[PDB]
Amino acid sequence: IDYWLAHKALA
Image (cartoon, one colour):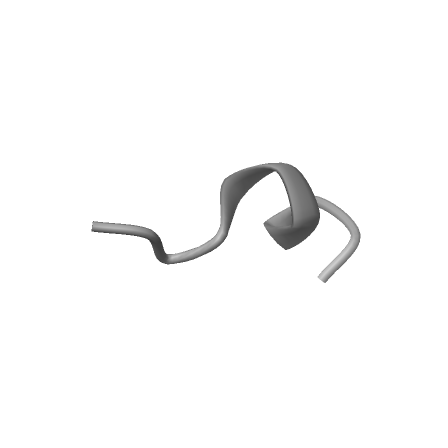
C-alpha cells in the first residue's frame, strides 16, 4: 500500500 493511505479507492 504505502500510498493508498493518501489515495484510497474513494469514488
